[PDB]
Image 1 (cartoon, rainbow, N blue to C red):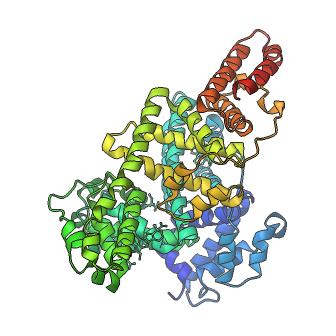
Image 2 (cartoon, helix red, strand yellow; image 1 turned 90 degrees about the horizontal axis):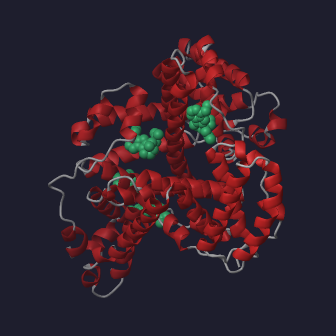
Image 3 (spheres, rainbow, N blue to C red; image 1 turned 90 degrees about the vertical axis):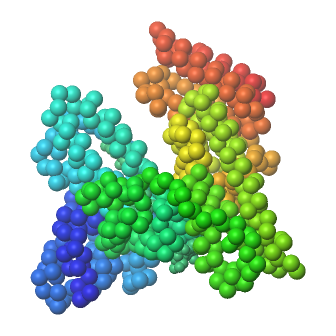
Length: 581
Ligand SMILES: CCc1cccc2c3c([nH]c12)[C@@](CC)(CC(=O)O)OCC3
Ligand SMILES: CCc1cccc2c3c([nH]c12)[C@@](CC)(CC(=O)O)OCC3
Ligand SMILES: CCc1cccc2c3c([nH]c12)[C@](CC)(CC(=O)O)OCC3
Ligand SMILES: CCc1cccc2c3c([nH]c12)[C@](CC)(CC(=O)O)OCC3
């Protein structure tokens, strides 16, 4: 286009344009205040309007990365606050943008955002545009790979909560359960999209395509191969652009894809009808989270073409990607009861069987039993989901999380206590989400969400690497991640952590904390116990943590809380060392 910025301005409209630009700037430089960003946004928008008037004007010819990057480099106190990004500003495009992306920050470690119901309603009423603008800023700078359009969607849910609850009788009780519900949903979108960006970064575009072929085929089993090809291609392009900070390009293609899917919903899925009767952002989001379609009656038998056919080696050798693509498509349609990564593991085994069999003297007799190689791949995760859900049903979320914190601290004791506690808690929430579902949905839910949690762990590991075992699981294979982490056991080389009694010391401040924040503190001690006594059994550790919980309960219920913690605390810390031998 003659002017790219004018094009995107005209298409998306001013409101979305300004939103997406705000988000973009908030993601790249997370430390600058909100009012500085507002000024950058306004300056870029004014330029787009000026360009939209006369597209042949000076500088309107420039690309989006040129104009956006130029703008980023004008920021006050750039070299001081972001030395790393200021190094990029000397470079030209496309080198500069690639430098910007390289030096983004997954753990900015900003202050936690408390929902302050009284004061936020006041700020909402006085200036809603500023208030909702601030929400975009605050979420974007804490989640640097969030997809712009999807954040704009969740901003409308946020606004809708504050219109409903601020005029109402009780401000907190209306708003708090809605805001925590919106948090959960926002965190899930973020986790999914970060996995897609992580898949590009670590494994490449081919990996994103294959994941997407598997998932879309499951969701849209009645869509023909060429239809799924079209959608995955466009979707992969959306992902690539949103992950590489091309937010205006991302919003446009994402909107076109939603439009396309809804134009052709009769040849894609019958579950899209309600999603397609919605406004722009609502529609895109609904499609992305649409339930799987019912299995077609006429799904083909696969043994003939993929196991029994006599010229598979020739067909495979002619074009591997097309042949395996076709296999993955067909096998994924008929298996909505498998996880995405299981399907990719099965495809990898299919490939491996043909690589082996087609080198042997009589290939067809070798590859005749190829589908039977899948049996042990299917039963391994089916057992672990049944085992863990049985455990979760028996003991509940808190004890299940503790079981996993012990499990993972033994695997990787070099990881920081906060990270181990975070990952064990997140992994435990998969039990509460998935084990309650119908049993045919348990496996996919579980493994699909474990992947999100493990990718979080892997991203944290890129920042602060501590363990070669984690690096191998994170970097070797996307499909093998969850099995790789499961296969890890206690490393027999790890030196048990130096005993500091201060680590296991509690005080009366714990008593006034919320129940979640109490658990976290106990769970942190649990991790530290494992670090000091790595060979202690899970039953020993559970028993000792029970003694910690009882101690905290009695002293928080005492007349003189601090005298109780001081007297009873050292006794418990000393005896607990002996109980963990
Ligand atoms: C005002 C409090 C609030 C309300 C609603 C949603 C959220 C989300 C968050 N806080 C919310 C956070 C931070 C911005 C939570 C986090 O990252 O821990 O990440 C987005 C969803
Ligand atoms: C149908 C199978 C298939 C086909 C083409 C490319 C890939 C890649 C993969 N599978 C492919 C994987 C998983 C997504 C393999 C892996 O990491 O184990 O990541 C690399 C590209
Ligand atoms: C166009 C709608 C859409 C269609 C089909 C699959 C997806 C997926 C997504 N959108 C999809 C998302 C969200 C779950 C990314 C996004 O937020 O845009 O991530 C992967 C799967
Ligand atoms: C190479 C990565 C790849 C992996 C798994 C399946 C597919 C499919 C494709 N690529 C795949 C294509 C092949 C035409 C789209 C494309 O890349 O042009 O269509 C859907 C099936």
